[PDB]
Every structure is written in structure tokens, then in C-alpha cells.
Image (tube, rainbow, N blue to C red):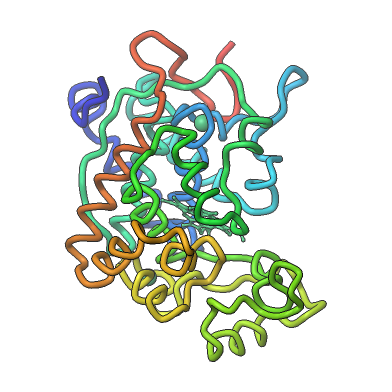
Length: 306
Ligand code: HEM
Ligand SMILES: [Ca+2]
Ligand SMILES: [Ca+2]
């Protein structure tokens, strides 16, 4: 069983070292907190939170970094290497990369103004990476609500609260124009924009992402508070201002009978959202972990120990 006190004797300073690393990085890269939370999400949705996403290519298995949901998108790997080295110096061969990334995600959320809590620990590192599984399990922005629900259920998160609360991760961070081009100019082959996108915001987004423009251009997920972790993401949805299709469907999908009340509840109360986010985060962090003597305590998060 995972426990928040796992390193209280072997490495009581691990959380502080992780925090310091992120604080320093945030000065030159204000997007790193968001990037790190996303790395944890993409780690957990593929064979569980086992740091499999951190592994680089080998001649026997491909890296998950080349998955459709990670390639030219996932970032912050060098920052993880940095905190891992700092932690390895303070506590040799003690903290797994899987746990390190989990702590990094929580600290990132807190540093951005979100809730503060101690995450369950005791996870161990995978002996391989899963590219095919990553391509199959990571949800895409063009997924319908039923598809989003299916994706979460597939990895073990059955609750609509899991989906709505965790989607709150889009309260900060960046998104490439490529992922909303259809919503802006030709949605579902209708030759028209997505009707669930506020028309005033549509104009703004079209200006940032013109047709035939730079598809890699970045746009803020939350137009209200782009870098602050808060409940503004849900207020946006209520106004049809969710950035990607998967965001807005939580409020506008024909299948949103169960998610709409959750969106409203989180928009109406920061406390309600924060409580739900921590609850959902710990549930995601509990997805099929390797524990005890299973797996290893990876020394270099990019490669399996030898
Ligand atoms: C519900 C399904 C979800 C879908 C389809 C989805 C999709 C996306 C997409 C398309 C991007 C943009 C990537 C890019 O343009 O490079 C992204 C970024 C991001 N996502 Fe999600 N996401 C989902 C759930 C989540 C969850 C559960 C979390 C975390 C709890 C999360 C956290 C983030 C963050 C923080 C960013 C910004 C990362 C950065 O700026 O580096 N996402 N997501
Ligand atoms: Ca994983
Ligand atoms: Ca925000």
C-alpha cells in the first residue's frame, strides 16, 4: 500500500529538494509547473505511475516520448533529471523516479497556487517503456465525451469526478494551434466552427491561429489566469470558452448530464474543486504501481539500472 510517509526516515528532505528545483526553473520557464503535472498524468495513464515515460530509446523497446500524445509536446525531462540528481546526492538510491515525478506534480500544483497535500509514496520504477500502450491509452483533444470517459475507465478511473476534476489541470499551461484548427474553421467536416465555442472567443482564437498559419504556435488553456492553478477553467466552460474540444464537452456534450453539475460545482467553489482535485490526483497516482521489491529504484530516470 502506498503511504505519504514512505520517505520520512530515508529521505525527509525529498519534497523540499523537488520544490527548490521547480522554484529555480520557474524563473526562466514559467510553463514548467504545468509541463511537470502533465508528465505525471501521461506517466500514470500508461502501465501506471512507474516512470515509464521517462525512459529513452533502446534497441529492444521504443520510448513513449515518440507517442502521438507526447512527441513534440511533452517537456521538462531535463528538469526531472536535475531534481533526480539532487535527490540522489542527498539520498543515494532511495527515491524512485515514479515517486519523484509524483511529488514534482504535486509541488508544481502547489507552487502555481493550487492545493497543498502529501502524496502517497512507495512506487517503484518500470523495467521497460510502453509506446504502443501510450498511443492507445492517452486521450486526444478530439475525443467525444464518451471517448474521454472510456479512456479514463480504461486505466482504472471510473468516476466522472475523476475526469472533470483532473481536466482542471488545464487551468494553466499551453496548447498548440494544431489541436483546435478544426474547432476554428472546419469542425467534424461541417466547414463551420464548433458551435460550442463562444463566438467572441472564436474570433480571438482565429487571430492567434489563422488558417494555414503556424500550427505549433502556443495558446493559453485558461484565458482568465493562464499560469495560476485555480478554478477559473470551469468558469470558462460555463461560458463556452473551454479551449479544446475535450474541455468544452464536459459542459456541452449530449452525454454531459453527469459532468455538468460537477463543472458548475467546481466553478462555484474553489474549495470544492481543490478537494476534488486532490482526491482525483491521489486516485490517478494509485494506478497499478509497482511496489515492494517489484521494479527498481532507477538511478538515472532515462535508463533501466544495469
Ligand atoms: C481529459 C483528457 C485530456 C486531454 C484530451 C488532454 C489534452 C491535452 C493537449 C492537446 C495538450 C496540449 C499539448 C501541446 O499542445 O503540446 C495538453 C496540455 C496539458 N495538459 Fe492535458 N489533456 C487531458 C487531461 C489532462 C489531465 C488529467 C492533466 C493533469 C491532471 C492535464 C494537464 C495538462 C497540462 C498542465 C498541460 C499543459 C502542459 C504544458 O504547457 O507544457 N491534461 N493536454
Ligand atoms: Ca507509466
Ligand atoms: Ca488558471
